[PDB]
Image: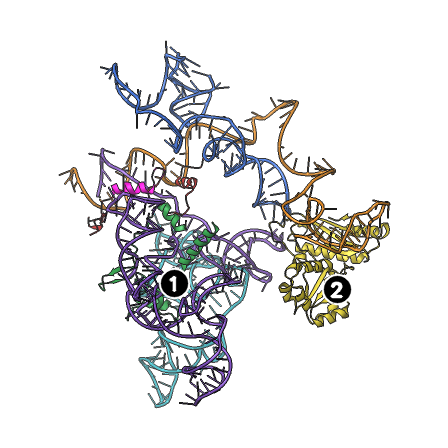
Chain colours: A yellow, B green, C red, D purple, E orange, F blue, G cyan
Amino acid sequence: ITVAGVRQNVAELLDYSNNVKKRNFLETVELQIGLKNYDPQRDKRFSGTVKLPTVPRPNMSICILGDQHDIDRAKHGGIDAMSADDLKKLNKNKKLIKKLARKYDAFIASESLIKQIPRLLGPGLSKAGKFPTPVSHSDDLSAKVNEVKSTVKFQLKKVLCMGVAVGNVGMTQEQLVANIMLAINYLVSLLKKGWQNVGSLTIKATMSPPKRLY
Amino acid sequence: ETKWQAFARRRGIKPKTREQRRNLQYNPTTGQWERKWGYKGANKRGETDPIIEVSAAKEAMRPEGTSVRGDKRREIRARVKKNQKQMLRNQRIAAEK
Amino acid sequence: GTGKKEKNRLLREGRTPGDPHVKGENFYRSAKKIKTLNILKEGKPIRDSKGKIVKAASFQSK
RNA sequence: GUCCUAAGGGGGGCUCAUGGAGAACAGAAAUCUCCAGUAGAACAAAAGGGUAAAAGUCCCCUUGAUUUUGAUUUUCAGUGUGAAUACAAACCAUGAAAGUGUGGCCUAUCGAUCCUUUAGUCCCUCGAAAUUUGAGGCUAGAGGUGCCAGAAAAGUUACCACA
RNA sequence: AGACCCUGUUGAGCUUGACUCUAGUUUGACAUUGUGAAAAGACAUAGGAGGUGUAGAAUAGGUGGGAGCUUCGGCGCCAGUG
RNA sequence: AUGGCCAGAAAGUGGUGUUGACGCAAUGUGAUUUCUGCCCAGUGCUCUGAAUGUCAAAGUGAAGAAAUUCAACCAAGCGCG
RNA sequence: GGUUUUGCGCGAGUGUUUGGGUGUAAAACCCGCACGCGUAAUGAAAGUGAACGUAGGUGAGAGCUUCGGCGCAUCAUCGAC
């Protein structure tokens, strides 16, 4: 995979998403991956998280799980939060946890409360793929929120098809290039043999026709 | 059917008679009747008699703190541990069956 | 076929590997038959070079 | 590393953990006395209803460590007075007695200087040089014959021969 | 210095699913090996059509974006089951 | 008979064979008289009847940069019937 | 071809005789390069490589002594590289 072909694909993607057809909401640029020379049904399923240079998802919500100081930090940061007494009033209610996982798209929990997540909420968030990100008492909450927003995962499921929201149309071309290149390089580094295990790479927007790279 | 029972059925090993498997034997040296195992059994002979002679190489290779008055109990515990290892393996296989 | 060796015969008959066997077992001879025929051959003591009995015969235990 | 007339069984007597109030040393915590104490102690199991003049704890007696018989059950027996096994009956132990209870539990064996397996990034070498696989060496770990490999080179000679 | 018995790192003849081999036999492949026709199976596409164990519009490929699509009839998140 | 039974290190080699089922070869029993304890179907004898179950070499496909590894396909016999 | 002991030469060296020169001719005499063993060990290997001290301290120890001690070989022991 070279430079200029992917740059041309990104430029055509932006041209179609901005000039040819524009919706009433901000579209999201996604990368879809097919894998060859590897099968998850007989080998170990890998996982990994990487911080993109730019925040790919603008329309998402983050749920903060912490004490009253964490709630104060969250209301300074402008992010909603819910407390441990609400965790006990939940008490592993499967329907409420399902609704919370369907509503909130990212979760962040403090280090003094993340030990109570399997005791009170169980493995529901880990099953749904929205397990909360640990944050310490000295870390900047705004920086941690930005890191969680820019962080995408490449966990290997039971199927070959993979999808990562790498960016959005509201970005610029160079930042979309940076996000796509970092995601591709992280996936290559996660793969055992690099480009040999890559089957096909495809980039598109939410309402756009796809463009093939590999 | 356990592993020993299958092996004995294959090899034609007859079960012992009740007189043969008694916990009783005649000690000639003392001229007395003694038990093969159990309380004051013959498998712990010399653990309480006043004198045991020991080998110099055996005492050199013996770890510190351990005495000669516990070697027979050590061997007994090793054999007993192997016996329950086999018994638990047989029980697990029978439970799977 | 499979082979006329005794190992091939045991594998064909599905015997348990590592089992002991009596010397002389083959396709025609089981352990019971071997013991029964060896009864007819027993009865001679083991001797040294000068004829002294070093191991007694069966049921002659001295 | 020390201790035991073993456990088990039968019978009898007693009630525990804890709290309150009392007693020279004795002072949260030593022992004794009373009261209250559904077991909150102990013993087995894993109650969503185990056990209180007991299934707990101490005394008395047995401790004989695996009885005898069977034409019956199941398996086996080139050593067929049958053996093992199940069941039954008798015996036995205890108790004044009604009764209660015992007359076993298991398992192929062999290596540990063995077998299987893992790691080395900043360990060494692959000898014309370099890189990447690979291989060998050296070092350090893990586990233990279910998933630690394997463990099948017989006879006869009255046709004979030699030392 | 026979015969008999005893011993052997014993010798030799013979037998047999004893061990390892082997003559013969049988089967396949390559070559010798040239000149022409005709079938069948398997993979690939250019693709088309499907897919209920239960619950649940749907007979649930799954995955990622997604609350909006909208060809103007409406389809949708939301509600419910997994 | 492009056969059977043999032989030879092999051969454009030999025998049976100057042979052809009333023949050749291999067995067992052993003149004549008598004679087939009764019934099967475990071992064996033979059926190209379906299977790929086992399945060698050669050949085919995939991965890798290659050494190499992994897959099917897989004759006879064995296995099943 | 080893190993221990005896005698001999030389001695941190030692061994002329594969070969050359020479000869009164298989003798004797002479010559030297390389090489063998020894002079350094250890490590699988890459590799590295033996003085703190009058080449150390303590106790013995023949012999000598200026009669205070100096102390061979060797032994035990603590150190150093």
Image point (75%, 57%), residue name = A179
Distance from the alpha carbon under mark 1 to that under mark 2: 63 Å
**At label 2, which amino acid type do we have?**
Asn
Q: Position of residue A104 (x, y in %)?
A: 73, 60
Of circles 1 and 2, the one toward us is 1
The disc at residue B77 is: 1
The chain containing the residue under callout 2 comes to A
Q: Rate crowding at label 1 as few (under 14), some (14 to 19) or many (20 or more) other CA atoms within 10 Å.
A: few
Q: Position of residue B74 (x, y in %)?
A: 37, 64
Is label 1 in a helix, a strand or a loop?
Answer: helix
Residue D98 falls left or right of residue E42: left
Residue F16 falls left or right of residue B50: right
Residue A46 visible in the current orientation: yes
**At label 1, which amino acid type do we have?**
Arg
Is label 2 in a helix, a strand or a loop?
Answer: helix
User: Range of the magenta residues?
Assistant: C26-41
The disc at residue A146 is: 2
> Which quarter of the figure has residue D66?
bottom left
Q: Does the magenta segment cover residue C35?
A: yes
Image point (30%, 43%), residue name = C35
The image shows residue E42, relative to residue A101, as above or below, that is above
Residue E70 falls left or right of residue C32: right
